[PDB]
Length: 164
Image (cartoon, rainbow, N blue to C red; front, side, top):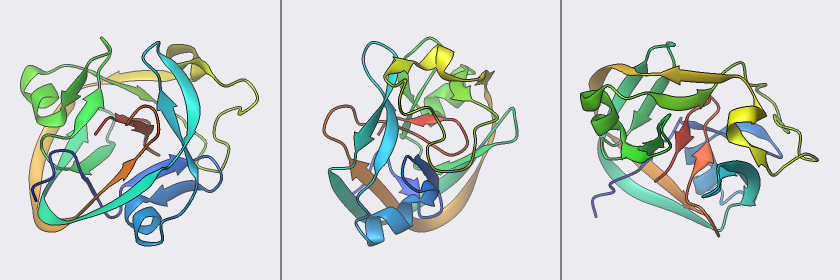
């Protein structure tokens, strides 16, 4: 079936235990690990993955942000905006809204202080508000997703917060 919010194989999730890892690998090997997620209150916390989804193949597009980072996902994949809405990346692009991202993130395990979590996202690190400046199709590619016990969202290695 068509997956509204899926990511490319190579999309790196910032895992707590292992650092940046492609979602394709996490799903292919059903890797048990934790991700950094945001709760309804706006706090970042660690969450263990509950399910792994290989959704087959579908069009994947590369969205480029103002800071040069890229997001390779389905057009309806939601991301956290600066005004704290979870909107489709294509919508964020069409409306020229800003994605709420962290920048200068350590690309290793325990990128954030596990001891201090939960902690407010806007105070967890250097916040970088960026718009989507372009989109280009990558054609039909493999797509993935993961399931979480509480909130279905997680921090990507590039600082963006993917929200299914």
